[PDB]
Image: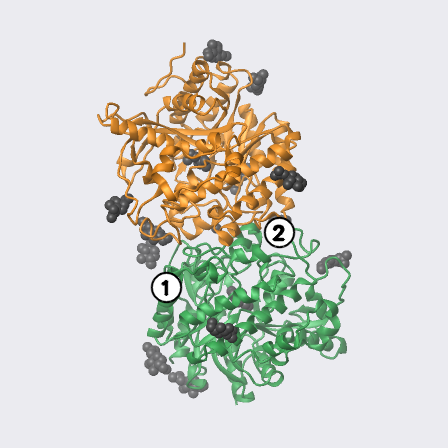
Chain colours: A green, B orange
Amino acid sequence: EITCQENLPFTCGNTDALNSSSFSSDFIFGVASSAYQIEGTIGRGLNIWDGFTHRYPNKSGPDHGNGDTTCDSFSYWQKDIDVLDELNATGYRFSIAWSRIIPRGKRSRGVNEKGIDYYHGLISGLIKKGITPFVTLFHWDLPQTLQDEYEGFLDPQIIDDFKDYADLCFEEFGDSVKYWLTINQLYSVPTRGYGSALDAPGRCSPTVDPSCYAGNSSTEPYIVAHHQLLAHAKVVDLYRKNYTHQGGKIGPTMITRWFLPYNDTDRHSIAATERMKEFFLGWFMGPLTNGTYPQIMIDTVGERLPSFSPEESNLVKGSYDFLGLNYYFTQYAQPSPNPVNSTNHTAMMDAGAKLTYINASGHYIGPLFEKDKADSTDNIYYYPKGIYSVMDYFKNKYYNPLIYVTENGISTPGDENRNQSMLDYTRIDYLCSHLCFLNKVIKEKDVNVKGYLAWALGDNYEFNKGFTVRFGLSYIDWNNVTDRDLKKSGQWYQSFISP
Amino acid sequence: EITCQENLPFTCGNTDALNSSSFSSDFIFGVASSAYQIEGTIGRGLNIWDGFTHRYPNKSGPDHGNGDTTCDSFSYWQKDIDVLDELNATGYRFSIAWSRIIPRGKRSRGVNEKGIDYYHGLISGLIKKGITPFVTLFHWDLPQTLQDEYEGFLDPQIIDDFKDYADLCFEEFGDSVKYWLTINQLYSVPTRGYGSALDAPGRCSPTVDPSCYAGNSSTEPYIVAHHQLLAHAKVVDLYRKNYTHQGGKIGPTMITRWFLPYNDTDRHSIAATERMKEFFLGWFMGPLTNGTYPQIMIDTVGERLPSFSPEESNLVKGSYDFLGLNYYFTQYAQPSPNPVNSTNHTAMMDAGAKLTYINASGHYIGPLFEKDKADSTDNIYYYPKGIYSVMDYFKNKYYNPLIYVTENGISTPGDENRNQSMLDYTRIDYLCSHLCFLNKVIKEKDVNVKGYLAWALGDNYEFNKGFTVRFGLSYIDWNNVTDRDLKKSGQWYQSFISP
Ligand SMILES: *[C@@H]1O[C@H](CO)[C@@H](O)[C@H](O)[C@H]1NC(C)=O
Ligand SMILES: *[C@@H]1O[C@H](CO)[C@@H](O)[C@H](O)[C@H]1NC(C)=O
Ligand SMILES: *[C@@H]1O[C@H](CO)[C@@H](O)[C@H](O)[C@H]1NC(C)=O
Ligand SMILES: *[C@@H]1O[C@H](CO)[C@@H](O)[C@H](O)[C@H]1NC(C)=O
Ligand SMILES: *[C@@H]1O[C@H](CO)[C@@H](O)[C@H](O)[C@H]1NC(C)=O
Ligand SMILES: *[C@@H]1O[C@H](CO)[C@@H](O)[C@H](O)[C@H]1NC(C)=O
Ligand SMILES: OC[C@H]1N/C(=N\O)[C@H](O)[C@@H](O)[C@@H]1O
Ligand SMILES: OC[C@H]1N/C(=N\O)[C@H](O)[C@@H](O)[C@@H]1O
Ligand SMILES: [Zn+2]
């Protein structure tokens, strides 16, 4: 019988009690990254994260930081492999920058052979060290040209451009890459990129944020989400029809959260919690498992929710061999109005829920996850059992999928000095508390989870936050980025992997 | 009788002997800038100077500097107006960033009203201080989308996109702007952007520079130059047919240089010198005055030189109300082979000339203009009489045009500290020596020159050099860019203007 802690102090950092041998022999352990965040612009075209951070610097991060040079994994990819080798990691999730291999967006305009060579070397070096690649085709860094030609995922033109890009990746790298992820966190671009405009490309309704260059927060999230599903599905069908000889697997990445009622004896809060599951997870998992959006979304969103034709439904339903599930935290849900006629209406209001980390009786759900110094009542708190709840829910509700945990991790503040940042015991407690629950759900619920990739391999540019927070298991000095030095968490993870 | 100095020491910094009253009463005096170099990316889309400096950082400058923030004239445009007001300047040349007003390149994709507002405020503030704007529509900063859709000026699609952009500028700002420049230095994009790949977009033949993403240095300069002439001419015809009510004037900007024989008793060097005039100046001035390229270019370049149809010839011939002539220096020319079959052949080799600053008897042409610490035999030297020679030549060869000197200036090294940089006596000597010759040619040759705009208003990002050199008449601290403090040269220029 496995017992896991939900509250500080944690004791799961003792590798005598929790280690890789606690999991099945074949279980993959590693770390994750993405291309905007780590490579730098050298050698690639420009994408919408370049565009957004440069046009709206105060949205790039409080320090106005961006991915121009970052940790320079363009030059120092071997040092990333060395970190993985030091960890004895068996997996590494990274992304391919579309703008590095097809700087002009549309594949007929030519490829960047040097870009292709950069990923070939990375992939070869990973394999030579026994590290299985998990490659994300699209971690948000859309070539700027596509955004400017047709507003990217807002237009159905994205489908074929994304398919031709994907096809080039499978042709060039699929002999060695056997695990592909299509779009990172399907929920995030529609809502943050086209709803709140916190993320690239930064579109929204005028009264949501007057800085947005265009948009409609009420309708565009749905359009973009629908196009993401179609583009994803077209790529999975291409992979499974044209690249079955490579013997690999493909899936989407979901951001997952658990949801609990803000008041667990209040029917209205319970109903909001179930609505959040459908609006946050079912918005994509209903299409992916059934070819349709959830009924509550059909009902509430009405004419703003696109329909799938019968062909599209069939393309999307079942369009995965596995699911990459990212997991960081859980929210309490309570009812909230949905003012659909308000000029500041967003798609995120359609769920009819307000989300918090404190419940009605004043209980904070778990330890601190992210401090927000400008408004401390907006602090995020984590909830280790949420990983158990999410995996259980996916098995039960979503037809027993094969799952890889493709991100899990926690930041520490960029204001800490190097010594403080290296002594990242808060990160060991976060990681180990989640791994304990992950082992527990695999054993108790028989969830088909086959690997875990912690966020992040190293310190990097953090979307929305610049370099004001650090997520790495290895530390990078921004005044001299060559080295990636294992923190206390990296050193702990090394011992967890090889106890 | 006017006597002007050609060699150090100069004495023309004494405003008792040379000042604005030496020139006609109506003569315009001011300074110049360009939008990439001064504004920053905030509030605009991305262009090919963003793309080039980010993809090829070692070509942006030795410091890898770029125009991301620069002197932040987006925020501090009023401080630029204050500099001009302090100078009592009567003119200011600046450029409009296409990517600020039409971030998506093609006007039908929408305009950026806030971008438009930024130039309206600038223009209104200039006029309120009695400063005549001279506005460059295109100072090299092509929206990246156009480069990625069709390779920008490489394709004839540029013509209409540039025309629709220009039309928006005339509609929005032409009620107040009465002097328009179309393309900055017609020679430079074809040769540096598409020949040597020193400049955006960075195309060349593979053996010229293996880093180029595509190109052909032998043919693409000609294609691009031809499209520039067509696009320029289409915009001048639009201005003169549709905006004649505004009562303004439009012209191209030429980079001018004088050329002298490396050996003035050697027929071969004399012939090379005359070939350089045709290949450097006549490449554009033959079309602009006659609708045809020079005969020597027709003969030498052969099938690589595009033809104008009769309609195009007529559009281009006479497509100026004035000429903006930039002038910085003069070269000696000697013969050089033109290996047209060599894989590393460039269009610049077609003139059959090698250019130096030292003649056959060892004479350096004038004072130091730019030191090149990596190869000192590549140092540039200036030649004050060259401004006289150029203006005389334009009057005699090119049908007595109306001329504004739209750039003239000199750098000082970025390694100097602030005190040294403020004590920029070398810049006073450069400026005054040229102004003396400019007054002399107006008086002696009756050249129709009506104003002079020194490069630059302030320190800025220098194409190819980052922040490793300074050109300003006012100093900017890169650790805190708000202020623009007049240097010794700005203070001298103030007294020259108002003696
Ligand atoms: C941040 O920048 C935008 C311009 O993109 C401006 O509209 C907004 O007010 C600024 N935000 C703050 C908090 O100052
Ligand atoms: C607009 O929404 C903001 C946050 O969504 C809210 O504080 C404000 O009341 C809303 N305004 C109206 C008119 O509903
Ligand atoms: C930068 O870091 C690398 C790795 O530690 C080191 O070898 C190199 O000397 C350092 N550079 C400077 C300038 O300190
Ligand atoms: C500069 O960068 C390019 C890659 O864009 C590389 O090909 C070239 O060798 C580097 N130049 C030098 C002098 O190192
Ligand atoms: C290529 O040109 C470079 C400079 O233009 C020159 O030094 C070299 O000789 C040329 N090579 C050939 C094969 O002509
Ligand atoms: C920056 O320069 C401006 C102008 O001199 C000054 O007012 C402001 O205090 C300076 N900022 C800092 C942080 O020094
Ligand atoms: O916020 C941490 C990490 N979290 C993420 N999702 O939750 C992103 O996919 C990744 O790019 C980001 O850096
Ligand atoms: O090199 C000085 C100056 N010289 C220029 N031409 O000669 C450019 O138009 C301008 O952008 C550049 O900064
Ligand atoms: Zn940048």
Residue pushed farthest front? B310
Could you classify mark 1 by the number of other residues whose Cα lies within 10 Å: few (under 14), some (14-19), or many (20 or more)? Answer: few
Q: Secondary structure at mark 2?
A: helix
**Residue lying at 53% horizontally and 24% vertically, measured from the top left:** B87
Q: In front: mark 1 or mark 2?
A: 2
Residue at the image position 33 percent from the left and 36 percent from the top: B351
> Quick check: B90 above or below A411?
above
Instruction: Look at the image and tell me whether residue B108 can be seen.
Output: yes
Query: Which mark is on residue B109?
Result: 2
Q: Which of the numbered marks, if any, corresponds to residue A117?
A: 1
The amino acid marked with disc number 2 is Arg
Left or right position of A202 against A29: right
| Element under disc 1 | helix
Image height of B441 relative to A403, above or below: above
Chain that bears disc 2: B
Q: Quadrant of the C terminus of chain A?
A: bottom left
Residue A314, given in percent of the width and then of the height, sits at 61, 79
The correct choice, above or below, for B210 with respect to B191 in the image is below
